[PDB]
Length: 322
Ligand SMILES: OC[C@H]1O[C@@H](O)[C@H](O)[C@@H](O)[C@H]1O
Image 1 (cartoon, rainbow, N blue to C red):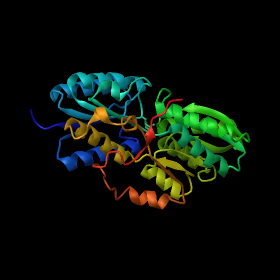
Image 2: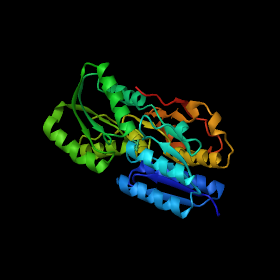
Image 3: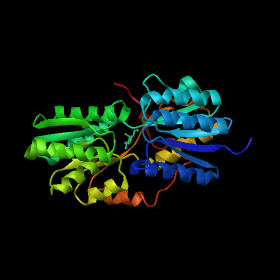
């Protein structure tokens, strides 16, 4: 019986969102002096669960996992594996509607998320304002089955209903990848040309991919684009006028807090069974970012006040399901 191992599972190191997510976990392990293990699936749900199992075995269950499930289906099997191993796990973003932490006390510590319908409608509303409320819009979505992809898209469709002057030219999935969004933006410009008066992206990486295509056609900054994540590269694009808005989930914080909750549960520092539901399944507070407050968000992400000890400081409310 040695030290507890802290592990963080996520899709890829190529998306700055996860670069920070990983940084935060790394920083939390650092603070408590526990070994850290990053796990990257690279899009393979099969690899992600395989790795988690391999780790659960080498630690004899003495593990605290903070994972962002590749797909919502993966969440249940991961949670089942941790539960039988006696390990503790926290979920981020993706999970089935029926999967609740309170059904797996105390191993399934918590699920963290944000209201994608609200924020998606927020970035979409800002985008349409920029367009004068009229014009053609193309939209890039995340992995089809992902909960945030579904919610943010739902937020978009709602902003559209409130702006009948906006015409949705075409919605396409780019799986959160800028390299997949690039060629899609190109084909849209060839297909719709001047009809495109704006671009909505389900996350920053895809927006930057969209902006790379615009830049290649000398339109970067002339066609308003929005994203979500609030990643440093996304923030830079906002200060430069190329991205009109984004939403900061604070991946750094997400990465560390997830493990913090899990570790405190394992140490019996918190009484899981007695926590309100909104502390088990939480929608967290995020920061809408635009040029007016971009400088403040940038400064935050270079001098992060790692509030690991204050577990429920950002609980906006419980996760809701339409
Ligand atoms: O797994 C869900 C996450 O996937 C990331 O690629 C994306 O940047 C996040 O905003 C969230 O959608």
